[PDB]
Image (cartoon, rainbow, N blue to C red):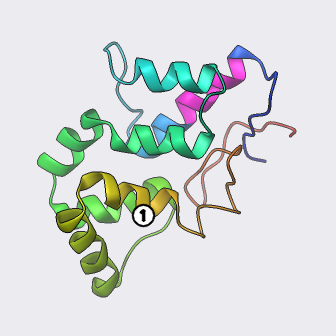
């Protein structure tokens, strides 16, 4: 049973969104004790942005980029962006080459947005429900 945000929902649940999104996007329990995304987290807390646009900002974070693009191969970084935002693996080299070309021609931002604004991410996780890896869920919210 996944996590959903709605209007009037409590601070513990919104911080549980931030924890779940971050843990899903970076994999190994993310980065805190720093500036990070204090603006984006306040927009989620204020209800100014959707959960999709929050997850987009966490996958746009430079603390995700320096750790998984610079300390790891770009092909593997695309393979990470799939399992982190969609919950799948791009075993097709045509699929990896498509996102590599988007990454170089339209930038880091456009590649990340290709996962968030995709029809597989949308509908299944919607604007209110938090994305998870296919096979992982340990924070059940009744609705």
Is residue 69 inside the magenta stretch?
A: no
Q: Quadrant of residue 133?
A: bottom right
Left or right of 119 on screen, residue 111: left
Mark 1 highlights which residue?
114
Q: Position of residue 120 (x, y in %)?
A: 60, 69
Q: Is residue 74 visible?
A: yes
Give the structural element (helix, strand or loop) at label 1: helix
Residue at left 67%, top 55%? 125
Q: Nearer the viewer, residue 110 or 30?
A: 110
Q: Which residue shows up at 34% across the image and 85% down it?
A: 92
Q: Main secondary structure of the magenta part?
A: helix
Q: Residue at x 80, y 36 (%)?
A: 141
Could you say where residue 102 lies in the image, as x and y percent from the top left? Answer: 27, 69
| Farthest residue, direction right | 142
**36 lies above or below 128:** above
Please indicate whether residue 23 sits to the left or right of residue 77 in the image. right
Q: Say which residue appears at 27% left-offset and 84% top-offset.
A: 93
Magenta residues? 12-20
């Amino acid at each position: 049973m996944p996590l959903e945000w709605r209007a009037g929902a409590s601070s513990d649940e919104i911080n549980a969104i931030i924890r779940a999104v971050y843990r899903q996007v970076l994999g190994n329990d993310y980065v805190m004790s720093t500036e990070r995304l204090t603006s984006a987290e306040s927009l989620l807390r204020g209800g100014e942005i959707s959960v999709r646009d929050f997850v987009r900002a966490v996958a746009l974070s430079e603390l995700y980029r320096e750790k998984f693009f610079h300390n790891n191969a770009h092909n593997r970084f695309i393979e990470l962006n799939f399992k982190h935002l969609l919950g799948r693996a791009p075993y097709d080299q045509a699929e990896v080459a498509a996102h590599a070309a988007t990454y170089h021609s339209h930038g880091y931002d456009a590649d990340i947005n290709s996962y968030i604004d995709s029809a597989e991410y949308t509908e299944s996780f919607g604007d209110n429900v938090v994305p998870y890896f296919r096979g992982l869920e340990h924070h059940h919210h009744h609705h």
